[PDB]
Length: 50
Length: 39
Image 1 (cartoon, rainbow over the protein chains, first blue to last red):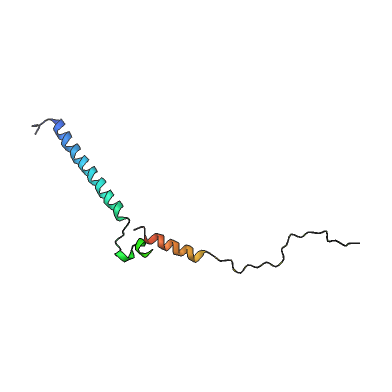
Image 2: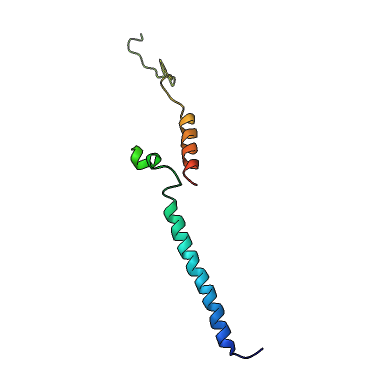
């Protein structure tokens, strides 16, 4: 309805995008950590077997 | 006269090939292991 400045809408939209990107970073970090487990039992992990 | 041998030949004597191993099965095992740990 044109009741706020357009710079306020731009800032809010950019904030949403930035939050999405930060969430992506966190998710990929967690996925990277899970690459070393692969959901196997404790005795099946390579180090314990070695 | 021919007292000392003076000829060469490009063919070996007494070739033995047994005890030479083929590495296919171990390569299959390696592929299987690598595929299991990639997800």
